[PDB]
Amino acid sequence: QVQLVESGGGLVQAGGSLRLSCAASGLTFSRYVMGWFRQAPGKEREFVAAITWGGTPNYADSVKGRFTISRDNSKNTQYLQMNSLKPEDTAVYYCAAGLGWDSRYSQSYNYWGQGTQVTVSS
Amino acid sequence: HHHKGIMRTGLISFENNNYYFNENGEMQFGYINIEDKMFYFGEDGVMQIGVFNTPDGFKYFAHQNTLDENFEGESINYTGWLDLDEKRYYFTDEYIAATGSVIIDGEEYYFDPDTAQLVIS
Image (cartoon, rainbow over all chains, first blue to last red; front, side, top):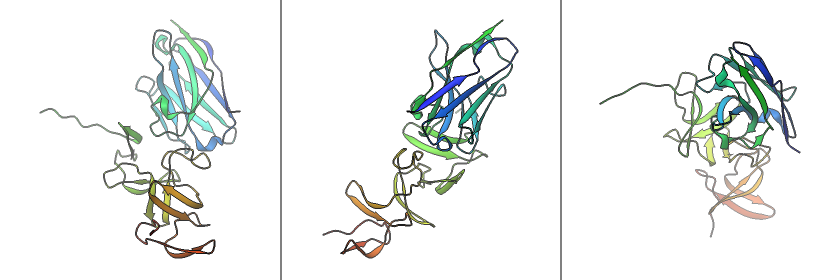
């Protein structure tokens, strides 16, 4: 009943760009903080970026300045623009929607996407 | 000693205490509008859950998803009787807490003008 669909993933060259899309159905989209997390094999799932119901964004330290998050409340869609991509950025990326306090934290989110592979080659 | 000045912005948690810092890194207190959701912060900055006095009347700031998929601590459009442990309240059509003497379903009640909690027994 509640679904978050990632797309826009896949393979890219380093220094190149990707635009991740997350499509939301089954909830009043305008009410949730929307976020992106990533898990690279070998590593723990880590916060990437988040956006408020009013469009105020915030980012993990290591993507700050390179990534830009945004939301289209009229299309139930949020976007992660990924620029200056690095081999460090290789991970499954997950969108999430949440009502919990601190954006930076997995437990602040109650709805999760399936995740999409982003591979970056040197 | 050793000290460094940092900056915190936005919705932040320290342990189990929730804060909101504005753009300029300044902690917020009392009845606060964050992008048009209303919240209540104690005199020590800590976000509160429960019924608190506002210019708009006594409001219920509630845990996430209490009503209409509301955000942690947001004021909600609650109506009817509310029990928050031993404290009882009654919310009007106007989504604020009743205060003073009122007749509800043919019985008379009194609610404290300073807290809105029912005075029983």
